[PDB]
Image (cartoon, rainbow over the protein chains, first blue to last red):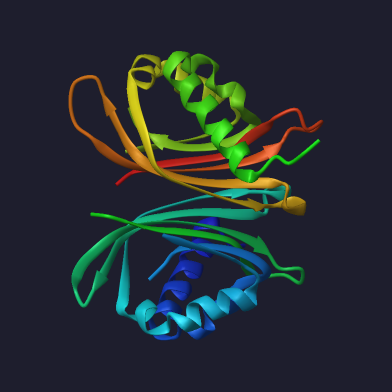
Length: 130
Length: 130
């Protein structure tokens, strides 16, 4: 008995928190074959949890230093049997309390092959100029 | 038979989409799957499901939608969904009406191949202003 809102709130809460405390563990939220498109800390495109881990690990200090504040959130069911979830978030990235850029991010979450959990199969995030 | 890239596909789709929006919004719905979900701009937001409801949205708001001027600043895409055959697009840019203010927007689409593979249909569409 869980709502799409319940799942997205909990996922984004946990994801963004992990981003602030330990980027080296962020890859755990992704599927094995996930794809990530991320502005560099000009975008990088990588595929697979291992490469995604290398990207977040190599940029660990910079990931932790840019704090994300969410301004909008939207989601919809998608994909096979409408069981996946599309999320779009927008907001602002701050460096020790100073606005650096806006962000736009989308995720796709795919339910796990066992049950209650979701994995990210797709993540696109762009930092755009204020 | 191929050599067709994800970029070619996405650039064609967006060109066709925004061109139809400019010329005849009453026919926009035909780009959507029958059970597509749209989360859009109140002419705060409107959520609608199904091609018939999507068509009532664009047709009722016909004068506003058609007089829009639009420029894309970023376009990102990845494969997703069943067998990696669907496409996630996220585009940002600017949007304005004949007279006055300039709005930044973020839009995401998911495109799924039609049953016989004639077209990529929109299953999901989300747009917000930032």
